[PDB]
Length: 52
Ligand SMILES: [Zn+2]
Ligand SMILES: [Zn+2]
View 1: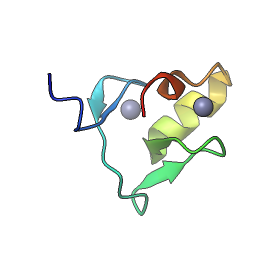
View 2: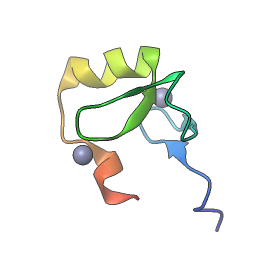
View 3: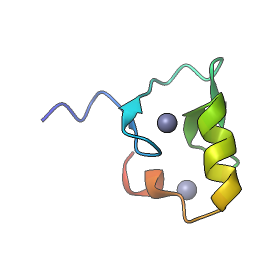
View 4: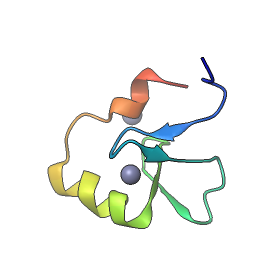
């Protein structure tokens, strides 16, 4: 399984290490701008913490 290539669990979309487009969460996770709003809206436990 291609786990070496990251994905956005916030909405099952694509994601990459480049944080110029992807906003950095203060816990070190990346998500596209809109998804930063979506996630921060909930303030829920960051699922990305399971994958690194
Ligand atoms: Zn997303
Ligand atoms: Zn985290």
